[PDB]
Image (cartoon, coloured by chain):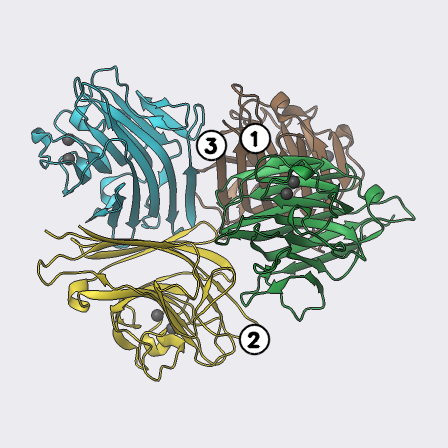
Chain colours: A yellow, B cyan, C brown, D green
Amino acid sequence: AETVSFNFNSFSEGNPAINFQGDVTVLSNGNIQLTNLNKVNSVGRVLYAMPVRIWSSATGNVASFLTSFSFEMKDIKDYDPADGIIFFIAPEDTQIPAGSIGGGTLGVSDTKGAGHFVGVEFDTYSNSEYNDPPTDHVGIDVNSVDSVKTVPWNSVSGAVVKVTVIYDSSTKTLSVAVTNDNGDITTIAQVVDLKAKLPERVKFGFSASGSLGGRQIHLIRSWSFTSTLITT
Amino acid sequence: AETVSFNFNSFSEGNPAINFQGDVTVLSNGNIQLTNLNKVNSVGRVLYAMPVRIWSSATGNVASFLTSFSFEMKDIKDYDPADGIIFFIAPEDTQIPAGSIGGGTLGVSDTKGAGHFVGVEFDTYSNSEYNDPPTDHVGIDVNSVDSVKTVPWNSVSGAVVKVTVIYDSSTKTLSVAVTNDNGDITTIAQVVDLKAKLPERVKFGFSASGSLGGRQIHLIRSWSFTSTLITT
Amino acid sequence: AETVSFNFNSFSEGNPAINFQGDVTVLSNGNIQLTNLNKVNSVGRVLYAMPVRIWSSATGNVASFLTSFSFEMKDIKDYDPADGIIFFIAPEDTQIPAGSIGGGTLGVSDTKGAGHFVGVEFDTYSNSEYNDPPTDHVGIDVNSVDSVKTVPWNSVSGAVVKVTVIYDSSTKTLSVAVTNDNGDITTIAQVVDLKAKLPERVKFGFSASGSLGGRQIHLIRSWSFTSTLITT
Amino acid sequence: AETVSFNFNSFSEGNPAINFQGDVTVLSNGNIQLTNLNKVNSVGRVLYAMPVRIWSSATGNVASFLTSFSFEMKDIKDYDPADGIIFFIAPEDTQIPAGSIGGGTLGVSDTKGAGHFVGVEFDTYSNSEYNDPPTDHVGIDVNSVDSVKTVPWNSVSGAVVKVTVIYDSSTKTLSVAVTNDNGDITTIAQVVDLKAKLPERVKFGFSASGSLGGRQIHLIRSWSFTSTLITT
Ligand SMILES: [Ca+2]
Ligand SMILES: [Ca+2]
Ligand SMILES: [Ca+2]
Ligand SMILES: [Ca+2]
Ligand SMILES: [Mn+2]
Ligand SMILES: [Mn+2]
Ligand SMILES: [Mn+2]
Ligand SMILES: [Mn+2]
């Protein structure tokens, strides 16, 4: 099999294994801060530099993967805690959409919420323009921030949140488990065919954004990942 | 929400939180050895002592859970490395079946391979009587050791294996991710309705067994668990 | 390390982790009401259902523990605001004393004020028979409601009180910090050798009582707990 | 009674309620980073600007206090994770010792490890000149870094550690409870006569230091405090 695995206990902005896009900044404690606090419509994205072959057009096999990460979102005075973080998967040439409005597009889609990526959002602001649930929520997005499926959640300012993700290739099921700060766990699962939605080679990463009047601290603290593709 | 959570980084004799059934022994290093290498048809089981309420007849909700543990199986001179470990979920009254032959029943089934439980097995011996695949394998068992779904695998003597299971209550999906010592991961997923196969209160634990001639070391090294039921 | 920890932000009817004894009620809000307002000499107690092993007889170790909870007492028309709440530790077989008069026994002692427990009381009525100080008070009780030590305090009808307690195994010091409504803190500390007054396995919980004439609302709103026993 | 109370969820540089001394800096996420990873004998300290009256001259009364704070220490590549953090109480005119060597003096003592203060350390490096135990430990310092009493502990890089301190005036008892990332708790308590060791008015705070070769990220994330002095 073809296995790809890495693990970041802390990041740095001079590492060739990480692509930075937008307002991304690495702090002295090793955390990655995706948005710029005093910047209007800020957008920041981080991507594992190396593309991962998630499927083969030769065999027809699709990879299974397991990945976990921890983030922190914190309020800043006089600003609406918005807009959220999104763990996404996209073609290897992915870029911040041209003329991005940041805000509720999460840095992955255009104005009407479309784009080419599959992902899991931790949305903290309800945009009715994207059919947002009326509360903080966790959602499964397939080429659009108009979530295929959402689950009410609760973002607690200043808390370290841990996430564990499993995609089983045979059932093509993507399931998510969020351990909150009060101990409670939140899960959400959805069947997504990666082969049909994405190309053979892709890039995984995180993206956060905000608007004018809607901003908050978006930090990524750690990240480990392992994918395995059977070559037979 | 109703949450149950715990974490064992080692075990000790006399902790009211754990129930021991059969040939279980607590090693001086904090590990739990499931079977007796000197007994024929050995069976050892360990359970979280408190029943967990997995679904409510009042509301109709089903809990979601995330649990992870790691184990090790090691070969012993002269005996066939058999038969394996199984993480299971059973009614509150659960006990080692009456006339257990151990062996391929894994300590949770009768002689024909039937019982009342839902569980994940790590089978190191192929029993044609239970329709086992020809190689070591990981399997999803619903009231039978004749697995509803299996996936090839390879037990390595002395290797520590780490496992992650996520049960998403809404899709009723149970997913597993196994991390071999070599780095490659193994996954298997299956929709299993817990509300349909089990009582409101259940118990969680691990079971292992052997035969005459089929024997090996079965160790549980750690276990963490968290379940959350959306209360009324 | 052998650790037990739990967190109840709210309570629910039917949870396997909570034992109710006497006049206990779970309100629609998740709060627990310890006494019945229409009953003479009412008593209600709520306990963490699992026995916790506080000291080991193998090694000579006693566990340290940190617990916090919040309660509220509130006046009811025409009745004297009595008698108070008590957070206690008792042998795992603990039960409301046979033919209990409620009142100043706080539901944990007998008519003479004796019993088998260690506890911190939030006493709202002065019982000269148990040598109560003349004002409301916080007391440390060792097998009796005639406190080993008390400190004046003031109960505010409808106020949410927060309490933190730390037991340090090495010195044997039980420390209590009470945070009133007006922000003021009240403290009390006492050396109590738990290994000499209690059995290895105990249960933790809250008890409240009233009499004819003496009645008020007794609520438990939350409770978190963590104990760690050095096993080695 | 005279009560002083505050609660910080994040700190800012333009805050006159806090005194910054030494290499201290405030990150964009609101954390206080006590040391400079680039400086050789970095020393950083942060003090609550307002002096607290811990005891009275008229009445021999001492104050009781309850305080809780969280921190995070993390390793940096090519440097020994040293030297630790210390919560301390000292004269209102306190300043970093002249010609401070950082290191094992924790920024509160001179070269022989002497000074005027009373504190709780989370020492991550073993200095024999100050008779340090051989492992990571928590200690009670009374005018010296050669602890009056210590307890073994473990500092986990990247982990958020919460602490709770209660000082009870009547028993003159200081006790601490540390919650590792693990769920496990460590406690330590000691009888310190605050009126015999410190002046009427004092300042509360934290300090951290490093050496050449010994350096790590030392952060303070939050801090709440309350103290009450009976003036009768
Ligand atoms: Ca949105
Ligand atoms: Ca078998
Ligand atoms: Ca009384
Ligand atoms: Ca030191
Ligand atoms: Mn959304
Ligand atoms: Mn099988
Ligand atoms: Mn009393
Ligand atoms: Mn020291």
Q: Is mark 2 on a helix, strand or loop?
A: loop
Closer to us: mark 3 or mark 2?
A: 2
Q: Mark 2 points at which residue?
A: A78
For residue D59, say whether it is visible.
Answer: yes
Report how far apart the C-alphas of labels 3 and 2 lie in the structure: 47 Å
Please tell me in which quarter of the rendered image ligand 7 is found: top right
**Residue at horizontal 44%, vertical 44%?**
C13
Report how far apart the C-alphas of labels 1 and 2 lie in the structure: 46 Å
Dot 1 surroundings within 10 Å: few (below 14), some, or many (20 or more)?
many
Mark carried by residue C50: 3
Chain hosting mark 3: C
**Residue at horizontal 19%, vertical 63%?**
A194
Vertical comparison of D19 with B98: above or below: below
Q: Please give left or right for residue C1 compared with residue A61 in the image.
A: right
x and y, in percent, of residue A162 in the image: 41, 54
Query: In which image quadrant can residue B90 be found?
Result: top left
Amino acid at dot 2: Asp
**In this view of the protein, which residue sits in the foreground, A181 or A201?**
A201
Q: Please give left or right for residue A81 compared with residue A109 in the image.
A: right
Amino acid at dot 1: Ala
Mark carried by residue C63: 1
Q: What element carries label 3?
A: loop
Q: Which of disc 1 and disc 3 is earlier in sequence?
A: 3
x and y, in percent, of residue B80 in the image: 16, 23
